[PDB]
Image (cartoon, rainbow, N blue to C red; front, side, top):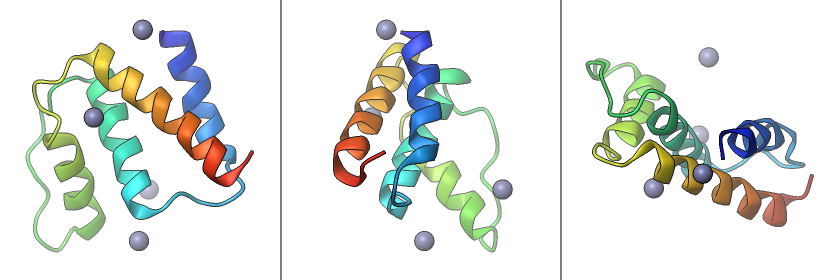
Length: 86
Ligand SMILES: [Zn+2]
Ligand SMILES: [Zn+2]
Ligand SMILES: [Zn+2]
Ligand SMILES: [Zn+2]
């Protein structure tokens, strides 16, 4: 649910270890897909390293329902809580 999405988005900030880059990109891309929906921005230039990585993670999800992105986000946070602790 949207309320559980809000809770997961809070809990992910309090993991005992910072998530890996792969995990951070999963979390970012699914967050954008669950909120904005399909990507609606142009890709950053080649030297915007963080920006283009973020954009790619969201772009890969094009066509995914907001409800599925939200479910995946929540499930990922639960996985991270078990992996790192909170
Ligand atoms: Zn739901
Ligand atoms: Zn890194
Ligand atoms: Zn920043
Ligand atoms: Zn996904």
